[PDB]
Image (cartoon, coloured by chain):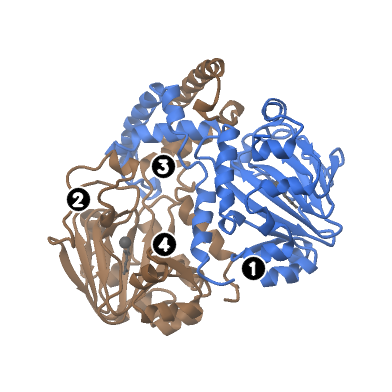
Chain colours: A blue, B brown
């Protein structure tokens, strides 16, 4: 059958069904034999923890209660060498091998293809990540501003999934162990947080060969009683706001008045403060008039902008680090 | 209004702010003991000391890297323990965010930021540069500004007034002169400078010389023999940065603006028409909120992140400060 890699994996669900009833809002669980994952380019290289370790020349994130206890409560995660990560792994810390696509770079082709098949803006952030855990490790209840296609490779992993009644379309991460909401999030958080154990969540056991589509914003937590290994393909979720502000900035960056250095008005004398306010009024009027002339075509024309400079910077930095042998 | 005074004397801080900052370079010569006023200066006064304290990836830059990478790149990050090998091959070493290891200097940098009237959120750091054997950086301009303190050796700087772009918002290497980033293209005027910046000012920076290097000024560097310098590097956030931050904060509360965007030419004709009306409506709302913008709201955003490239690198490096390289 002339099928896409994604189609091959979610069969007998069609890609149209996926796009109409699941993406980008509802989770999908697709079960089957792990061998159908072998059409993912580079899968054989990340099929076992020993294989991932043989190729992954980068720092590894470790997360969990052992980190909280060692750090005397300062943090729940460290970035460490692959070797040290194995020491933490034995203490039940979850290991995250981020930007695994640097080390199976053939998957990058596929990811870009999948990004187009999902009709994501070209500029959307995308990567592969490997997650490994044992001894009850994993992640406590949280949500992400990203969506994931999750391919369970080894072991049985317990996911909790709950609808998020507090925020629609979150644009930042949040750990439920913060109960305090960060600034932007505070502006659109509604209602009471869920309990730490997500008591109303759906529990899903992921086994080898299970693919889980995980939409952005769902509350989730993970636990690996025994050793597990999974490969995630992780996508940004650029908002209309992202594209609109990129388009507006493209219209304004040409104007030297907008490129001039900004000034902290705090130290200024009152007359200078007022003059700055009049200068800024001029800018405000011009910004508003450029916003008023914004068109759909211009918004679409900025779909190839960098909407996640945090992810892009982390990719560049990790690429530069490959010159050290971790 | 005091921190720089003893270093740029006889230039006064008022003269510096009115006549030089943020557009024209200044060269202040004097005794290097001046620099003892900077917290932690003793700890970066030789390359040995820097290497003793700097527990982070070190950037190495130059011909030796071009060779090792078979032409792919001129830079990469290595361990402090491997950096000296590259230095001996004439690669320039960049110890980025050196202020992570001399925390003392943060207070100083913050005072300077306040003195210069920079937005509170402006990026700011210390960087040490070391090179020998003709190593350094080829002709380019930065979107950052730098206060440069020459500690050791005689370093050849070329400096050239930028006649092409005012207040650039990104980095540019003169060597890429066929190609121009889209944004830069939209405000570049005229022809790029000539190869090797023939009309440049040549300035030999000797120990105790401080160079103020404004954003956008063309420069390049060469260390014939060993050199060591400390930079204090500041972002240059534009009014556009604060204003778009303020506008985003007004809109991020509205779920319509947080909804997932789509690839235009992936969807059907019916869908392509159905998106136009929704986007026209959103554009109306964006415009209405832009018309509500006040100077107060712009200033209330001065503590935002205007430089995710720098902030991201800082967080990453902070997670590596006790890494066993
Ligand atoms: O895989 C895990 O243990 C945790 N993964 C996530 O939270 C995620 O993919 O967003
Ligand atoms: O110090 C050097 O050799 C090069 N430095 C710069 O380009 C800079 O400070 O912007
Ligand atoms: Mn998650
Ligand atoms: Mn420079």
Label 2 or label 3, whichever lies nearer to me, is 2
Image mark 1: chain:
A
Q: Is mark 3 within 8 Å of ligand 2?
A: no
Q: What residue is pinned by disc 3?
A: B241
Instruction: Give the alpha-carbon distance from disc 1 to disc 4, as whole Å.
Output: 34 Å
Q: Earlier in the sequence, mark 2 or mark 3?
A: 2
Q: Earlier in the sequence, mark 2 or mark 4?
A: 4
Q: What residue is pinned by disc 1?
A: A80
Q: Up-down: is A8 above or below A298? A: below
Instruction: Give the alpha-carbon distance from disc 2 to disc 3, as whole Å.
Output: 27 Å
Label 1 or label 4, whichever lies nearer to me, is 1
Residue nearest the observer in this picture, A114 or A38:
A38
Q: Position of residue B308 (x, y in %)?
A: 48, 50
Q: Secondary structure at mark 3?
A: helix
**Residue B216 visible somewhere in the drawing:** yes
Point 17% across, 60% down: residue: B197
Q: What residue is pinned by disc 4?
A: B111
Instruction: Give the alpha-carbon distance from disc 4 to disc 3, as whole Å.
Output: 22 Å
* For residue B179, side relative to residue A130 (left or right): left
Same chain under badges 2 and 4? The reply is yes
Label 4 or label 3, whichever lies nearer to me, is 3
């Amino acid at each position: 059958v002339t099928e896409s890699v994604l189609e091959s994996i979610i069969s007998p669900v069609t890609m149209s069904e996926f796009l109409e009833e699941y993406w980008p809002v509802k989770p999908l669980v697709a079960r089957g034999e792990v061998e159908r994952f072998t059409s993912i380019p580079g899968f054989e290289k990340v099929r076992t923890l020993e294989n991932v370790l043989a190729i992954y020349n980068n720092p590894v994130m470790v997360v969990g209660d052992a980190v909280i206890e060692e750090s005397e409560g300062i943090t729940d995660r460290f970035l460490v060498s692959p070797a040290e990560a194995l020491e933490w792994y034995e203490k039940g810390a979850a290991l995250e091998f981020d930007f695994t696509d640097l080390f199976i770079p053939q998957v990058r082709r596929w990811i870009e293809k999948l990004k187009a098949e999902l009709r994501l803006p070209a500029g959307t952030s995308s990567k592969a990540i490997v997650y490994a855990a044992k001894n009850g490790g994993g992640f406590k209840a949280h949500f992400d501003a990203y969506t994931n296609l999750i391919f369970q490779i080894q072991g049985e992993k317990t996911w909790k999934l709950a609808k998020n009644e507090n925020v629609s379309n979150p644009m930042q991460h949040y750990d439920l162990s913060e109960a305090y909401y960060p600034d932007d999030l505070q502006s659109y958080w509604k209602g009471d947080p869920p309990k730490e154990d997500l008591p109303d969540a759906e529990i899903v056991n992921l086994t080898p060969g299970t693919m889980l589509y995980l939409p952005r914003g769902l509350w989730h937590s993970t636990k690996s009683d025994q050793a597990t290994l999974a490969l995630n393909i992780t996508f940004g979720q650029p908002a209309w706001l992202d594209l609109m502000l990129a388009a507006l900035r493209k219209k304004l960056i040409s104007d030297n008045r907008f490129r001039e250095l900004a000034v902290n008005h705090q130290s200024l004398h009152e007359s200078s403060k007022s003059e700055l306010n009049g200068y800024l009024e001029s800018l405000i009027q011009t910004l508003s008039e450029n916003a008023e002339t914004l068109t759909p075509e211009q918004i679409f024309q900025s779909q190839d902008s960098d909407f996640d400079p945090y992810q892009s910077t982390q990719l560049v930095f990790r690429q530069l680090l490959t010159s050290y042998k971790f």
